[PDB]
Image 1 (cartoon, rainbow, N blue to C red):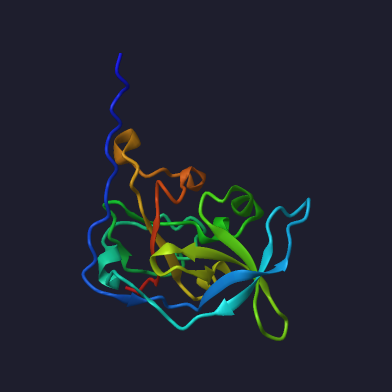
Image 2 (image 1 turned 180 degrees about the horizontal axis):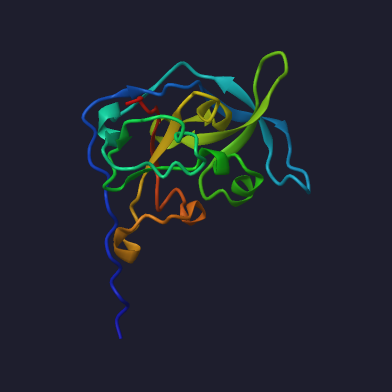
Length: 183
């Protein structure tokens, strides 16, 4: 008996403009400290890059549907909604956890910044611009940063889970990191 034909994936809509990543972006390639038994990932030295643009307009990602707002960072005031129809925000707080680092359902690197205190932060990889962005920066008090992905998995009728641990970069690749406008 033939194998079952899988349902085809869902593709993101095209972008209608460009949008510069509104937080600092970085290259993490040089190793600062090798993995240890308790920390099975290296720490990199973070090197700053000049700003880059995603190939979507901010308005492409915005609309009138609700953000998941997993970590409640957007709950304190009225924001422009999400475009929805497959676009959705990811949990920037979860992605900075040891758990998210162990799993690498998304590619996340730990790195040491330049500067007085030499802060060690977790950096989400952004394939769209092949560069890294600090989860610390995106989720800072009043930054109003959102990581926007697009749900591609046609399973369960294409429904987006209400459990962020069900997400991964193949099911839901990152499309952009934005500052969501107030409304």
